[PDB]
Length: 71
Length: 71
Length: 71
Length: 71
Image (cartoon, rainbow over all chains, first blue to last red; front, side):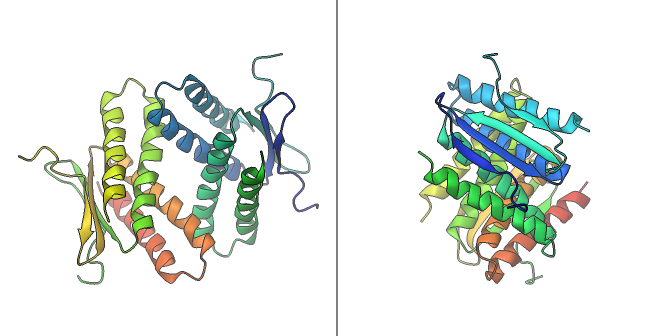
Protein backbone atom coordinates (compact mmCIF):
# COMPACT_ATOMS: atom_id res chain seq x y z
CA UNK A 1 0.00 0.00 0.00
CA UNK A 2 2.77 2.40 1.02
CA UNK A 3 4.75 1.37 -2.06
CA UNK A 4 1.88 2.17 -4.41
CA UNK A 5 0.65 5.23 -2.46
CA UNK A 6 -1.08 6.77 -5.46
CA UNK A 7 -1.71 5.86 -9.10
CA UNK A 8 -5.46 6.14 -9.31
CA UNK A 9 -7.48 6.19 -12.50
CA UNK A 10 -11.26 6.37 -12.73
CA UNK A 11 -14.29 7.73 -14.51
CA UNK A 12 -15.48 11.09 -13.21
CA UNK A 13 -19.15 11.96 -12.60
CA UNK A 14 -18.75 14.93 -14.93
CA UNK A 15 -18.04 12.62 -17.84
CA UNK A 16 -14.26 12.77 -17.78
CA UNK A 17 -11.49 10.41 -16.72
CA UNK A 18 -9.32 11.12 -13.70
CA UNK A 19 -5.72 9.96 -13.42
CA UNK A 20 -3.57 10.63 -10.35
CA UNK A 21 -0.04 9.21 -10.28
CA UNK A 22 3.26 9.80 -8.50
CA UNK A 23 6.98 9.43 -9.19
CA UNK A 24 9.96 9.70 -6.80
CA UNK A 25 11.98 11.21 -9.65
CA UNK A 26 11.61 14.37 -11.69
CA UNK A 27 12.98 12.49 -14.69
CA UNK A 28 10.22 9.93 -14.47
CA UNK A 29 7.56 12.62 -14.42
CA UNK A 30 9.17 14.50 -17.30
CA UNK A 31 9.51 11.28 -19.28
CA UNK A 32 5.91 10.37 -18.53
CA UNK A 33 4.61 13.65 -19.93
CA UNK A 34 7.01 13.43 -22.86
CA UNK A 35 5.74 9.97 -23.64
CA UNK A 36 2.07 10.90 -23.74
CA UNK A 37 2.58 14.19 -25.64
CA UNK A 38 4.47 12.32 -28.38
CA UNK A 39 1.63 9.83 -28.86
CA UNK A 40 -0.88 12.63 -28.57
CA UNK A 41 0.96 14.68 -31.18
CA UNK A 42 0.86 11.70 -33.54
CA UNK A 43 -2.90 11.53 -33.04
CA UNK A 44 -3.18 15.23 -33.90
CA UNK A 45 -1.27 14.68 -37.12
CA UNK A 46 -3.59 11.80 -37.95
CA UNK A 47 -6.57 14.00 -37.07
CA UNK A 48 -5.65 17.60 -38.06
CA UNK A 49 -9.34 18.43 -37.80
CA UNK A 50 -9.34 17.40 -34.13
CA UNK A 51 -9.31 20.65 -32.14
CA UNK A 52 -9.56 18.84 -28.81
CA UNK A 53 -6.55 16.74 -29.77
CA UNK A 54 -4.52 19.84 -30.54
CA UNK A 55 -5.60 21.53 -27.33
CA UNK A 56 -4.96 18.31 -25.42
CA UNK A 57 -1.51 17.98 -26.95
CA UNK A 58 -0.93 21.62 -26.13
CA UNK A 59 -1.97 20.88 -22.56
CA UNK A 60 0.73 18.22 -22.44
CA UNK A 61 3.23 20.65 -23.92
CA UNK A 62 2.32 23.12 -21.19
CA UNK A 63 2.38 20.38 -18.56
CA UNK A 64 5.84 19.25 -19.67
CA UNK A 65 7.04 22.83 -19.35
CA UNK A 66 5.30 23.15 -16.01
CA UNK A 67 7.02 20.04 -14.67
CA UNK A 68 10.33 21.24 -16.10
CA UNK A 69 9.94 24.60 -14.39
CA UNK A 70 8.88 22.84 -11.18
CA UNK A 71 11.54 22.83 -8.44
CA UNK B 1 -13.50 27.41 -12.31
CA UNK B 2 -14.58 25.67 -15.52
CA UNK B 3 -11.46 26.16 -17.62
CA UNK B 4 -8.69 23.77 -16.60
CA UNK B 5 -10.10 22.36 -13.34
CA UNK B 6 -7.57 19.53 -13.30
CA UNK B 7 -4.10 18.93 -14.72
CA UNK B 8 -2.21 19.60 -11.53
CA UNK B 9 1.40 18.78 -10.85
CA UNK B 10 3.29 19.48 -7.65
CA UNK B 11 5.79 18.05 -5.17
CA UNK B 12 4.23 15.79 -2.56
CA UNK B 13 5.90 15.13 0.82
CA UNK B 14 5.21 11.40 0.64
CA UNK B 15 5.03 10.95 -3.11
CA UNK B 16 7.73 13.36 -4.31
CA UNK B 17 5.70 14.50 -7.29
CA UNK B 18 1.96 14.31 -7.77
CA UNK B 19 0.31 14.58 -11.16
CA UNK B 20 -3.47 14.74 -11.57
CA UNK B 21 -4.71 15.09 -15.15
CA UNK B 22 -7.95 14.40 -17.01
CA UNK B 23 -9.06 13.30 -20.48
CA UNK B 24 -12.52 13.15 -22.12
CA UNK B 25 -11.55 9.90 -23.82
CA UNK B 26 -10.40 6.50 -22.64
CA UNK B 27 -8.38 6.15 -25.82
CA UNK B 28 -6.49 9.29 -24.90
CA UNK B 29 -5.72 7.92 -21.45
CA UNK B 30 -4.64 4.57 -22.88
CA UNK B 31 -2.31 6.32 -25.32
CA UNK B 32 -0.99 8.51 -22.53
CA UNK B 33 -0.13 5.57 -20.29
CA UNK B 34 1.47 3.84 -23.26
CA UNK B 35 3.77 6.81 -23.70
CA UNK B 36 5.02 6.83 -20.12
CA UNK B 37 5.45 3.05 -20.11
CA UNK B 38 7.59 3.33 -23.25
CA UNK B 39 9.97 5.86 -21.70
CA UNK B 40 10.07 3.92 -18.46
CA UNK B 41 10.99 0.78 -20.34
CA UNK B 42 13.83 2.59 -22.11
CA UNK B 43 15.12 3.58 -18.69
CA UNK B 44 14.81 -0.01 -17.43
CA UNK B 45 16.73 -1.26 -20.44
CA UNK B 46 19.51 1.17 -19.57
CA UNK B 47 19.20 0.33 -15.88
CA UNK B 48 18.24 -3.38 -15.69
CA UNK B 49 19.54 -3.32 -12.14
CA UNK B 50 17.02 -0.63 -11.22
CA UNK B 51 14.23 -2.43 -9.36
CA UNK B 52 12.27 0.77 -8.70
CA UNK B 53 12.39 1.51 -12.41
CA UNK B 54 10.88 -1.90 -13.08
CA UNK B 55 8.29 -1.40 -10.35
CA UNK B 56 7.43 1.97 -11.86
CA UNK B 57 7.17 0.50 -15.33
CA UNK B 58 5.12 -2.33 -13.87
CA UNK B 59 2.84 0.26 -12.30
CA UNK B 60 2.28 1.70 -15.76
CA UNK B 61 1.58 -1.78 -17.11
CA UNK B 62 -1.02 -2.19 -14.39
CA UNK B 63 -2.36 1.30 -15.02
CA UNK B 64 -2.68 0.53 -18.73
CA UNK B 65 -4.60 -2.62 -17.87
CA UNK B 66 -6.73 -0.70 -15.40
CA UNK B 67 -7.60 1.92 -18.01
CA UNK B 68 -8.41 -0.88 -20.45
CA UNK B 69 -10.90 -2.36 -17.99
CA UNK B 70 -12.36 1.09 -17.36
CA UNK B 71 -15.67 1.95 -19.10
CA UNK C 1 31.67 -6.73 -41.16
CA UNK C 2 29.05 -9.47 -41.10
CA UNK C 3 28.85 -8.94 -37.34
CA UNK C 4 26.74 -5.83 -37.81
CA UNK C 5 25.60 -6.42 -41.40
CA UNK C 6 23.14 -3.56 -41.27
CA UNK C 7 22.13 -0.84 -38.80
CA UNK C 8 24.04 2.02 -40.31
CA UNK C 9 23.66 5.76 -39.97
CA UNK C 10 25.72 8.30 -41.88
CA UNK C 11 25.67 11.43 -44.05
CA UNK C 12 24.02 10.87 -47.43
CA UNK C 13 24.59 13.21 -50.40
CA UNK C 14 20.96 12.68 -51.36
CA UNK C 15 19.36 13.01 -47.94
CA UNK C 16 21.93 14.57 -45.56
CA UNK C 17 21.66 11.73 -43.09
CA UNK C 18 20.88 8.12 -43.94
CA UNK C 19 19.56 5.55 -41.51
CA UNK C 20 19.57 1.89 -42.57
CA UNK C 21 18.31 -0.86 -40.26
CA UNK C 22 16.86 -4.37 -40.28
CA UNK C 23 14.45 -6.43 -38.16
CA UNK C 24 13.49 -10.13 -38.34
CA UNK C 25 10.06 -9.24 -36.95
CA UNK C 26 7.07 -7.55 -38.50
CA UNK C 27 6.25 -5.93 -35.18
CA UNK C 28 9.72 -4.51 -34.66
CA UNK C 29 9.59 -2.64 -37.96
CA UNK C 30 6.10 -1.31 -37.26
CA UNK C 31 7.14 -0.25 -33.77
CA UNK C 32 10.28 1.37 -35.14
CA UNK C 33 8.38 3.53 -37.63
CA UNK C 34 5.79 4.40 -35.00
CA UNK C 35 8.57 5.50 -32.70
CA UNK C 36 10.06 8.00 -35.14
CA UNK C 37 6.71 9.48 -36.20
CA UNK C 38 5.84 9.95 -32.51
CA UNK C 39 8.97 12.03 -31.98
CA UNK C 40 8.50 13.76 -35.32
CA UNK C 41 4.93 14.61 -34.39
CA UNK C 42 6.20 16.33 -31.25
CA UNK C 43 8.46 18.44 -33.46
CA UNK C 44 5.49 19.35 -35.65
CA UNK C 45 3.56 20.38 -32.56
CA UNK C 46 6.47 22.62 -31.57
CA UNK C 47 6.71 23.93 -35.13
CA UNK C 48 3.20 23.83 -36.69
CA UNK C 49 4.37 26.18 -39.43
CA UNK C 50 7.12 23.73 -40.38
CA UNK C 51 5.83 22.31 -43.66
CA UNK C 52 8.91 20.13 -44.13
CA UNK C 53 8.26 18.72 -40.66
CA UNK C 54 4.66 17.97 -41.57
CA UNK C 55 5.83 16.45 -44.86
CA UNK C 56 8.44 14.48 -42.94
CA UNK C 57 5.77 13.25 -40.55
CA UNK C 58 3.71 12.35 -43.60
CA UNK C 59 6.70 10.43 -44.92
CA UNK C 60 6.63 8.38 -41.73
CA UNK C 61 2.89 7.88 -42.07
CA UNK C 62 3.45 6.64 -45.61
CA UNK C 63 6.36 4.49 -44.47
CA UNK C 64 4.20 2.95 -41.75
CA UNK C 65 1.55 2.23 -44.36
CA UNK C 66 4.16 0.71 -46.66
CA UNK C 67 5.33 -1.56 -43.85
CA UNK C 68 1.73 -2.39 -42.93
CA UNK C 69 1.05 -3.50 -46.49
CA UNK C 70 4.25 -5.55 -46.50
CA UNK C 71 3.74 -9.29 -45.93
CA UNK D 1 11.92 7.82 -62.11
CA UNK D 2 13.35 8.26 -58.63
CA UNK D 3 11.04 10.50 -56.63
CA UNK D 4 11.23 8.34 -53.52
CA UNK D 5 15.03 7.92 -53.47
CA UNK D 6 15.13 6.97 -49.82
CA UNK D 7 12.59 5.99 -47.17
CA UNK D 8 12.58 2.42 -48.30
CA UNK D 9 11.08 -0.52 -46.51
CA UNK D 10 10.82 -4.05 -47.86
CA UNK D 11 11.44 -7.71 -47.15
CA UNK D 12 15.11 -8.59 -47.37
CA UNK D 13 16.23 -12.20 -47.80
CA UNK D 14 19.28 -11.23 -45.75
CA UNK D 15 17.48 -9.49 -42.90
CA UNK D 16 13.71 -10.10 -43.19
CA UNK D 17 12.82 -6.44 -43.23
CA UNK D 18 14.97 -3.70 -44.63
CA UNK D 19 14.34 -0.08 -43.74
CA UNK D 20 16.30 2.90 -45.10
CA UNK D 21 15.29 6.47 -44.20
CA UNK D 22 16.76 9.98 -44.44
CA UNK D 23 16.61 13.17 -42.38
CA UNK D 24 18.18 16.63 -42.85
CA UNK D 25 18.87 16.73 -39.11
CA UNK D 26 20.98 14.51 -36.91
CA UNK D 27 18.56 15.27 -34.08
CA UNK D 28 15.71 13.80 -36.09
CA UNK D 29 17.68 10.62 -36.67
CA UNK D 30 18.63 10.46 -32.99
CA UNK D 31 14.98 10.93 -32.04
CA UNK D 32 13.97 8.31 -34.60
CA UNK D 33 16.29 5.77 -32.99
CA UNK D 34 15.04 6.87 -29.57
CA UNK D 35 11.49 6.21 -30.71
CA UNK D 36 12.13 2.64 -31.80
CA UNK D 37 14.28 1.93 -28.73
CA UNK D 38 11.41 3.14 -26.53
CA UNK D 39 8.91 0.74 -28.10
CA UNK D 40 11.49 -2.02 -28.27
CA UNK D 41 12.34 -1.60 -24.61
CA UNK D 42 8.65 -1.93 -23.75
CA UNK D 43 8.55 -5.23 -25.62
CA UNK D 44 11.68 -6.34 -23.76
CA UNK D 45 9.95 -5.67 -20.46
CA UNK D 46 7.01 -7.72 -21.70
CA UNK D 47 9.43 -10.45 -22.80
CA UNK D 48 12.53 -10.33 -20.53
CA UNK D 49 13.40 -13.82 -21.73
CA UNK D 50 13.58 -12.53 -25.30
CA UNK D 51 17.30 -12.33 -26.12
CA UNK D 52 16.67 -11.17 -29.70
CA UNK D 53 14.51 -8.40 -28.28
CA UNK D 54 17.22 -7.36 -25.85
CA UNK D 55 19.84 -7.61 -28.59
CA UNK D 56 17.56 -5.60 -30.87
CA UNK D 57 17.11 -2.96 -28.19
CA UNK D 58 20.86 -2.99 -27.69
CA UNK D 59 21.27 -2.59 -31.45
CA UNK D 60 19.18 0.56 -31.17
CA UNK D 61 21.28 1.69 -28.21
CA UNK D 62 24.40 1.06 -30.26
CA UNK D 63 22.91 2.83 -33.26
CA UNK D 64 21.90 5.71 -30.98
CA UNK D 65 25.50 5.93 -29.86
CA UNK D 66 26.67 5.82 -33.47
CA UNK D 67 24.31 8.64 -34.42
CA UNK D 68 25.34 10.59 -31.32
CA UNK D 69 28.94 10.55 -32.50
CA UNK D 70 27.87 11.15 -36.10
CA UNK D 71 28.60 14.77 -37.07
